[PDB]
Length: 74
Image (cartoon, rainbow, N blue to C red; front, side, top):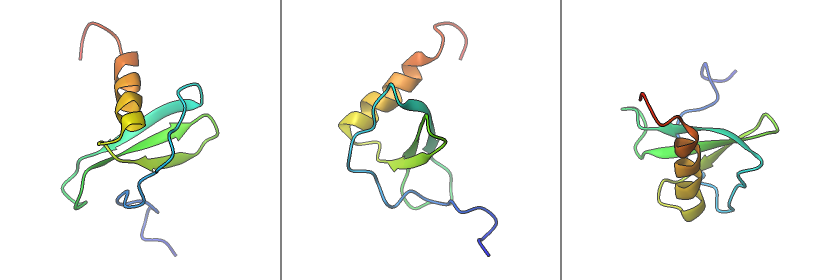
C-alpha cells in the first residue's frame, strides 16, 4: 500500500517542455518537507508532471499560469 498519498517531492524533473494549450493548471512546491523546491504541471488529460523552477518552459509556464490570474486582488 502507498504512504497515504503517492506524492512527496518532484525529484524526476521533466526535461521536455509542456505546451500551454494542453496545460490546465500547476502546483508549486515550497513546503518544509521536501529537500528542494519545485513545480508541478497539469495538462488537459487529468495527468500531472514534475517541473523545475529554473527551466525556460517552466518559467514561462509558471509565469503563464501566474499571469492568467486577475489584475486586482491577490
